[PDB]
């Protein structure tokens, strides 16, 4: 009983036994630890794409940058991660500077909102400003 | 092998006494950052190991033949410790040992 949670949510005679005898004498032919270490390399799920998505309050999360520039820098970061994972000074399998011209690709970013406009001012401040424009006070 | 060659004395003279043979780590133990303890501290320069036991797990295969790229990165980290902080101390040590007799190192 009383199981823990990963995330917070709302709350802030004689037995001779001649059968078995387990000692030794077989080695793993591709190798147990090596094949299962490859398996726990492959087991991990995909990391999330939370860019250009609303947060709790409603503002689009992520950095303010052009969509195409963010896609190209994201391919650059994947190439550098591939280089660090193959442990060379240059990733042999590269994701950027390929022969394919891909000057129209766009990965999502925090520049554009859900309605279709820019995020120079966040949506919470825009709504608060558009409703603080029309107020009225008590007379003197 | 030093204990075996210690106990030989043919014609009253001892053949290879212990008193003037130099062990491999005697030049390493006289330094104040004490070289083996100095190269235990190599793991902080490497980005993603940040522990000695994690380093010894990471360099190996779990077969005890190591990967070549981990040895290459650790050797690039290791070569300034062996060229700068070892060689002049070794010059002073082997010069001192050559001054105090004719020895075997």
Image (cartoon, helix red, strand yellow):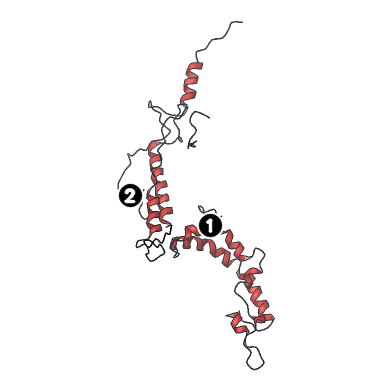
* Residue A91, visible in the rendered structure: no
Dot 1 alpha-carbon crowd within 10 angstroms: few under 14, some 14 to 19, many 20 or more? few
Quarter holding residue B25:
bottom right
Dot 2 alpha-carbon crowd within 10 angstroms: few under 14, some 14 to 19, many 20 or more? few
- Residue B65 versus residue B9: which sits nearer the camera? B9
Q: Vertical placement of B92 versus A23: above or below? A: below
Q: SS of the residue at dot 1?
A: helix
In the shown orientation, is residue B41 left or right of residue B71?
A: right
- Residue A7 versus residue A116: which sits nearer the camera? A7
Q: Vertical placement of B94 versus A123: above or below? A: below
Front of the two marks 1 and 2: 1
**Label 2 belongs to which residue?**
A98
Give the image location of residue A116, x and y in percent. Answer: 37, 27
Give the image location of residue A22, x and y in percent. Answer: 40, 62
**Label 1 belongs to which residue?**
B53
Disc 1: host chain? B
- Residue at the extreme right: B100
- Residue at the extreme front: A13
- Residue at the extreme bottom: B11
Give the image location of residue A92, x and y in percent. Answer: 36, 55
Query: Which residue lies at the image location 61% right of the left edge and 68% below the top edge?
Result: B86
- Residue A104 versus residue B66: which sits nearer the camera? B66
Give the image location of residue A125, x and y in percent. Answer: 49, 24
Please report contact status of discs 1 and 2: CB closer than 8 Å, yes or no: no
Quarter holding residue A31:
bottom left
In the shown orientation, is residue A122 left or right of residue B81?
A: left
In the shown orientation, is residue B78 left or right of residue A103?
A: right
* Residue B83, visible in the rendered structure: yes
Query: Which residue lies at the image location 58% right of the left edge and 59% below the top edge?
Result: B41
Q: Vertical placement of A13 versus B100: above or below? A: above
């Amino acid at each position: 009983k009383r199981i823990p949670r990963k995330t917070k949510g709302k709350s802030s005679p004689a037995t001779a036994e001649p059968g078995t005898s387990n000692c030794e004498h077989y080695k793993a032919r591709p190798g147990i630890a090596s094949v299962q270490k490859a398996t726990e390399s492959a087991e991990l799920p995909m990391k999330n794409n939370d860019e250009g998505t609303p947060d709790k309050r409603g503002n689009t999360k992520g950095a303010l940058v052009n969509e195409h520039v963010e896609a190209r820098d994201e391919a650059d970061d994947a190439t550098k991660k591939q280089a660090k994972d193959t442990e060379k000074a240059k990733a042999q399998v590269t994701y950027s500077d390929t022969g394919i011209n891909n000057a129209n690709e766009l990965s999502r970013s925090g520049n554009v909102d859900n309605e279709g406009g820019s995020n120079q001012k966040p949506m919470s401040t825009r709504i608060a400003e558009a409703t603080s424009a029309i107020v009225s006070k008590h007379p003197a | 092998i030093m204990r075996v060659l210690d106990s030989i004395s043919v014609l009253g003279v001892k053949i290879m006494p212990r008193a003037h043979v130099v062990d491999s780590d005697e030049v390493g133990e006289q330094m104040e950052p004490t070289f083996e303890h100095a190269v235990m501290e190599i793991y902080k320069g490497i980005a993603g190991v940040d522990s000695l036991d994690d380093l010894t797990k990471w360099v190996l295969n779990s077969d005890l033949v190591p990967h070549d790229d981990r040895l290459g990165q650790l050797f690039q980290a290791f070569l300034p410790l062996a060229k700068d902080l070892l060689a002049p101390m070794a010059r002073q040590f082997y010069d001192n040992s050559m001054s105090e007799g004719r020895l075997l190192t």
